Length: 340
Ligand SMILES: O=S(=O)(c1cccc2cnccc12)N1CCCNCC1
Image (cartoon, rainbow, N blue to C red; front, side, top):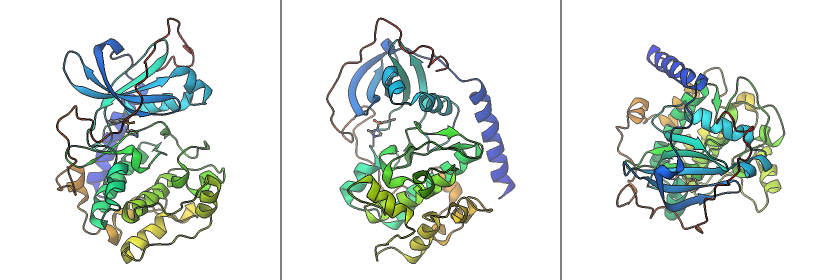
């Protein structure tokens, strides 16, 4: 580790801790925005393209229903998500611009990234070439180096959470499972195909789960499908815990070697969790052509630029029923969300 990297990360941690200890709160309100379109929807919230009525800027507004967050046992997770997002700063992490709450909902107003999910692009082309997968993987490696140095675990890496920006670079979204952890944590969360064995087996786990998930992501980008696939989750879990993985013959030997070390079922032997930390990944032969500083500085020409007409274009996102944003006349769950 060059003193240069050490000093960068020391400053990053100082700046994160100052915002972590004194979080911003209540920095806009709903009637500052016009609603444009629903971009995504889930069991306790949705994301909406909105336009600020005074500046004209577009944003992605995540709206969480407090009562559904409580029912689905996501209180601490939603508090983690906002407290972390308002404190971080890195080129490949989506920016939180405003946050607020009302009688019914929590609101996180983020930069709008018009290029769409990596998932859509991957499914449309089939698979990414190794150089193309490597460009995205390098951004995730650097992002995890940053997050883990702050004692943060991400826990939701998957192609649907990685958006492609106007320059073709990644923006990581969805901090709903991110957590500040010194040592181990225990919650069962994440998407089946991406879960590390130690999550499935109900162990106290650490940042090594993010490095496992990177292995799954690289495999899926390069093959077009994930390494452990089945019709039902329990069948997926049996494959994950087995210690067996099959690689397409078109994978390079270097790619297969990196993946065996990320998809290592013994967490004490897994790349990213050894004495040399992230450098076992950054120095691997599969990354020999990667200029880490040039990626960080966004000086590498991207594999593709998404096609879109302007900052309000939604063509790279898909269509959802447009439902009301109702705000109750009575405050709900005020105590639970006091710190938001
Ligand atoms: O609309 S999003 O939730 C989304 C979340 C957070 C920030 C965003 C910024 N720009 C666009 C979409 C965004 N998104 C697409 C549909 C669902 N998959 C996850 C990514």
